[PDB]
Length: 154
Image (spheres, helix red, strand yellow):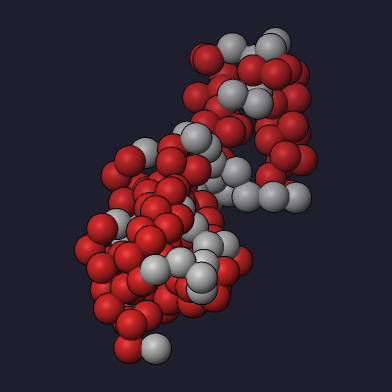
């Protein structure tokens, strides 16, 4: 009855007190407890109102985290966000924080390590491997070209 919505609110705050969660993560965590859509929606809106669920904030902190702790570029950061239930629109707004100059600087750092790793290759084969590595990590062609121009300066 009314103890349904109650159990729902309780599990939600347990799940959130620890880590940050996307709306969808909570939206289908209430289902892990067999709570109807009639009630999940009531719980979710209330949580959003109390700012306990906030996808813009989720996406922004994720982006800051990856910028600071990973070697991943915008494209991979975005698909990670999509895999968590973040709207494309919200992910895109959040990715605005990963400025070109910041991407290039992280890319130059990775490129420098790889240059040393492939130090025996020809300049051409060397850059191909580096561009390839940066592409699989999520950086765009233009960003990679700027990284390559930067690396040669070095």
